Image: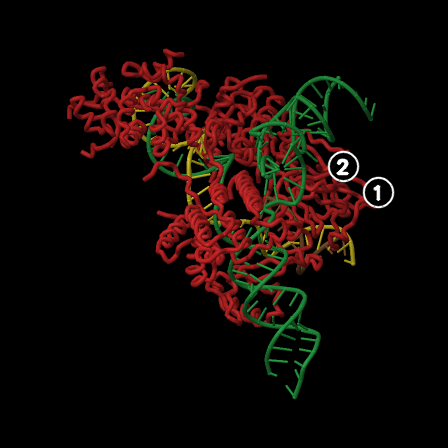
Chain colours: A red, B green, C yellow, D brown
RNA sequence: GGUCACUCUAACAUUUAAUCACACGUUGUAGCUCCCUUUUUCGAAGAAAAACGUUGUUACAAUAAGAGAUCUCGCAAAGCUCUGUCCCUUUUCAAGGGACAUCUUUU
DNA sequence: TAAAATCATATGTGTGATTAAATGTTAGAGTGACC
DNA sequence: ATATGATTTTA
């Protein structure tokens, strides 16, 4: 049986074939495949949303500028609007603003929009942003703070010294309703004084700007995610059909445990309770204890009888909304309407946009009723039952049948279904395990059954369950153990578990659940398994340690090489997110504002104004020395320089020899990822050209290679007098022999400054190099440096020296 | 009589995927402003200036680098229909099987 | 000294919304394969 | 985990 030892980073395996199953003789080969503060896709999604919001504000302000130009407010050129936007917004309530003052006010009320609530219509502990909009909305009605700007310049700037939010404080923020109110009042008051551009057309368009935001879920969105039995769409939970399915499932499975006997409801009892929770908001247990003439003990539960069996919350929510607003007559007609009642929960759960909800109910509910439901009702669940299959399977379970009986009356390894596995870790592990399985099938045929025993334990168990079921139920051209079972009898440990997982049976697992007795399924364990996986020896040293029973080795037995996933993607993070100042980049330095709460004395020693402002440097050095070089404890209260100004962050210089120009070419950021490295030789010397992601994106092929003691401009240039060996990606199989020694392994890192490389041992033997990684390896005078190749399992070790310099982009 | 797997229901815990917004923060540029290097003019202390650094605060612009049709992609993943490069079976070619991607898809 | 191995230091963040999907456990109902 | 500058030891 394939002894797959699953995992989120590695898949160890150990092949075994047994006669009569039961007692096994000996395995064939072993292997480990090692592939690779949360999922990297979360970073991509957050960056994507940030890009979308940034460009949407770009567009919104541009559109506002065009609108203002059309009214002859914003003259074509001369777009240097006043800076004192908040003060001018305050002044507009009492004086007339000019053309450009008003233009700045409008273009600024479009930028800082506010906060528009997007909660459900399910009306009736505040955080920071919400507790700031309310605490200012409760101050805007003091009649002394007529508008958010007036409150800002009369309360915020007066006491706190700033208007905008700062340093993670979510006070000083306002709701979009308050700013729209300011828009309206400003327009009206400017009409009172005579602003020519107070056109209410402009106000309507500007409210459209300051209020429009895309709905989060628009149309098929939910449908696009609901897709994963059968095939019809899974019904909503708040649908009368699904609600009655839950009710009948409970009632039929509501066995009565009385007098030590389990008795189902006879048809009389259920007919009594069939449609009972419809005339009451909740069917309590004591309510059942009366209608059915209970002999004073249910089935489960926990005389505190006041529990809930089944409340059709959907049914009672639609009424208490429609029963109000004097819409009694429609509900009475709608009290049955089983299709109609079903179709309102199918819409309010599948579509949330008011337009999209009104579309699904194609006038089938009166628009006066539809308005009330749109304004007061929301449904957001979904059940695991096709509604089409509900109309046929629910009637049978009315009282006479059960789910199992009702359904019966209605009666190599393929690729992992990606759409059904929307989690990159699980999908990656499953696909690499599938590749390993297909490889071992090719190398051995179908060995036997399969044996699998494995902060993200959720992902691991998703992988295990899905792999077991997929393997067992899929074929083309069976055992789920656990760690406790494995423990009974470097990175190579997954092989040992593999063997132990392969030498396992369902009988021992059941005996474990019922729990010396465990035997040895081989002639000898210690020497056999010690050299089989660990201490790799191709017979020989095995044979010297295997004097007795010289029946060892197989037609293909060889030492184990841990194959590692090749990463050859050319996309990634172009540059680091800390943007700096490149105005002094020619000096070789960057200038970044450093918060005082992180200004360690090391950082203070690189301040730009060290000697320009000597008194500042002296006092800052003293206070850091007074708190043991802990800026957080040192500058925990605002620092003050000579002259009464407050110091909150100081420009600090940093050593910048290599970087990326960003922000319109104004700033510089550190290199983030090195996608590929191109090797070259000239005069018996190995020179490596590093390539970064931003170079690939811009369509740039680097020329010069790494020179240790020189800067990027003075780096050795690869030209007609250089020989191109190959490219190098992270975790690439390379062979290195030098005058010092010989090492063969994986390549994961290039040191730009020193020029050294980081080569990693296949097994990550923690007694080898810098705990498994042979870091800082010099190859300038290397005898030979060749890129190898490896298969999924750790064999077919091929090498050449072919070349074609592949152009990025 | 047990163990385990699967199907449905409810409750709890956790995790993942997609979408809509907000508020900071960084950089650049102006206005005001805290300091403080240098150099002018009036001068026998001090004032008015100019360049550079730079503290705070307001406004405006960029917020990946970049690719496309006001508007869409761009840090993730899978794969072999199209494209490109390595590897094997039967100097080049042709078939078979596979590996990775700068190719396609999610989009 | 050139090249090489060692060490050492730094990485953008919090708030507020609509949803779907998966795993594990417990409670209830059941079928099916193996001890 | 990755990029890489500062510093020590080695050929």
Residue A704 x/y as whole percent: 76, 47
The local crowd at label 2, few if under 14, some if 14 to 19, many if 20 or more residues have their Cα within 10 Å, is few
Q: Identify the disc placed on residue A357.
A: none
Q: Are marks 2 and 1 in contact (CB under 8 Å)?
A: no
Give the SS element for disc 1.
loop
Image-based side of A626 in relation to A33, left or right: left
Please identify the quarter of the rendering in which residue A415 is found.
top right
Residue A164 x/y as whole percent: 48, 55
Please identify the quarter of the rendering in which residue A568 is found.
top right
Viewer can see residue A168: yes
Residue of label 2: A805
Could you say which is closer to the camera, residue A773 or residue B19?
B19
Quadrant location of the C terminus of chain A in the rendered image: top right
Please identify the quarter of the rendering in which residue B45 is found.
bottom right
Residue A395 x/y as whole percent: 32, 15
Give the SS element for disc 2.
loop
Residue of label 1: A720
- Residue drawn 52% across and 19% down? A474
The local crowd at label 1, few if under 14, some if 14 to 19, many if 20 or more residues have their Cα within 10 Å, is few
Q: CA distance from mark 2 to mark 1?
A: 13 Å
Could you say which is closer to the camera, residue A381 or residue A121?
A121
Chain of the residue that carries numbered disc 1 in the rendered image: A
Q: Which is more N-terminal, label 1 or label 2? A: 1
Could you say which is closer to the camera, residue A82 or residue A263?
A82
Could you say which is closer to the camera, residue B87 or residue A270?
A270
Image-based side of A511 in relation to A265, left or right: right
Chain of the residue that carries numbered disc 2 in the rendered image: A
Residue A554 x/y as whole percent: 63, 25
């Amino acid at each position: 049986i394939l002894g797959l030892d699953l995992g989120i980073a590695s898949v160890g395996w150990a092949v075994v074939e047994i006669d009569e199953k039961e007692n096994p003789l000996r395995l064939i080969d072993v292997g480990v495949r090692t592939f690779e503060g949360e999922s990297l896709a979360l970073s991509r999604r957050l960056a994507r949303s940030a890009r979308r919001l940034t460009q949407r504000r770009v567009a919104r302000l541009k559109k506002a500028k065009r609108l203002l130009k059309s009214e002859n407010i914003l003259l074509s050129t001369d777009e240097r609007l006043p800076h004192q936007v908040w003060q001018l917004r305050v002044e507009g309530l009492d004086h007339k603003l000019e053309r450009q003052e008003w233009a700045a006010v409008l273009l600024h009320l479009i930028k800082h929009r506010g906060y528009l609530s997007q909660r459900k219509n399910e009306s009736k502990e505040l955080g920071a942003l919400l507790s700031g909009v309310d605490n200012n909305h409760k101050l805007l009605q003091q009649a002394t703070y007529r508008s958010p700007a007036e409150l800002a310049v009369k309360k915020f700037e007066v006491e706190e010294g700033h208007i905008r939010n700062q340093q993670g404080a979510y006070t000083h923020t306002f709701s979009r309703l308050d700013l729209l109110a300011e828009m309206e009042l400003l327009f009206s008051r400017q009409q009172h004084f005579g602003n020519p551009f107070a056109s209410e057309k402009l106000l309507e368009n500007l409210t459209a700007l300051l209020m429009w935001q895309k709905p989060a879920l628009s149309g098929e969105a939910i449908l696009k995610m609901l897709g994963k039995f059968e095939d019809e769409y899974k019904a909503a939970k708040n649908t009368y059909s699904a609600e009655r399915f839950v009710w009948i499932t409970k009632l039929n499975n509501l066995r009565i445990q009385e007098n030590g006997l389990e008795r189902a409801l006879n048809d009389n009892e259920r007919l009594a309770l069939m449609e009972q929770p419809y005339d009451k908001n909740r069917l309590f247990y004591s309510q059942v204890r009366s209608i059915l003439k209970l002999s004073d003990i249910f089935k489960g539960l926990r005389i505190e009888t006041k529990a809930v069996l089944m409340e059709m919350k959907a049914y009672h929510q639609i009424r208490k909304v429609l029963e109000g607003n004097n819409l009694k007559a429609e509900w009475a007609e709608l009290k049955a309407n089983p299709t109609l009642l079903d179709e309102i929960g199918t819409a309010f759960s599948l579509y949330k946009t008011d337009e999209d909800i009104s579309a699904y109910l194609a006038g089938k509910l009166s628009q006066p009723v539809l308005n009330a439901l749109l304004e007061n009702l929301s449904f957001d669940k979904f059940i695991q039952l096709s509604l089409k299959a509900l109309y046929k399977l629910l009637p049978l379970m009315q009282q006479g049948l059960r789910y199992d009986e009702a359904c019966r009356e209605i009666y190599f390894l393929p690729q992992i279904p990606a759409d059904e596995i929307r989690n990159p870790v699980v999908l990656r592990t499953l696909t690499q395990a599938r590749k390993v399985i297909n490889g071992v099938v090719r190398l051995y045929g179908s060995p036997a059954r399969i044996h699998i025993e494995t902060r993200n334990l959720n992902d691991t168990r998703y992988v295990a369950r899905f792999l077991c079921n997929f393997i067992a139920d899929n074929m083309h051209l069976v055992f789920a153990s656990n760690g406790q079972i494995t423990a009974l009898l470097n990175d190579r440990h997954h092989a040992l578990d593999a063997v132990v997982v392969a030498c396992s049976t369902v009988a021992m697992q059941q005996k474990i659940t019922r729990f010396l007795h465990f035997p040895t399924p081989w002639q000898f364990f210690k020497q056999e398994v010690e050299i089989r996986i660990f201490s790799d020896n191709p017979k020989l040293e095995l044979e010297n340690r295997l004097p007795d029973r010289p029946q060892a080795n197989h037609e293909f037995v060889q030492p184990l090489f841990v194959s590692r996933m090749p990463t050859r993607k050319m996309t990634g993070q172009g540059h680091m997110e800390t943007v700096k100042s490149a105005k002094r980049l020619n000096e070789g330095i960057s200038v970044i504002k450093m918060p005082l709460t992180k200004l360690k004395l090391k950082d203070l020693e690189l301040m730009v104004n060290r000697e320009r402002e000597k008194d500042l440097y002296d006092t800052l050095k003293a206070r850091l020395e007074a708190f043991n070089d802990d800026p957080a404890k040192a500058f925990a209260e605002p620092f003050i320089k000579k002259g009464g100004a407050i110091v909150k962050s100081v420009r600090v210089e940093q050593i910048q020899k290599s970087g990326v120009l960003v922000r319109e070419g104004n700033g510089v950021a550190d290199n983030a990822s090195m996608v590929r490295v191109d090797v070259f030789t000239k005069g018996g010397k190995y020179f490596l050209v590093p390539i970064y992601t931003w170079q690939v994106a811009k369509g740039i092929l680097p020329n010069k290679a790494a020179t240790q003691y020189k800067d990027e401009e003075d780096w050795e240039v690869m030209d007609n007098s250089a020989t191109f060996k190959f490219s190098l990606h992270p975790n690439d199989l390379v062979k290195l022999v030098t005058k010092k020694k010989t090492i063969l392994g994986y390549f994961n890192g290039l040191n730009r400054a020193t020029g050294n490389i980081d080569i990693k041992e296949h097994d990550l033997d923690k007694s080898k190099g810098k705990q498994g990684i042979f870091e800082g390896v010099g190859i300038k005078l290397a005898l030979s440096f060749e890129k190898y190749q490896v298969d999924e399992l750790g064999k077919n070790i091929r090498l050449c020296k072919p070349s074609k310099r592949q152009p990025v982009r």
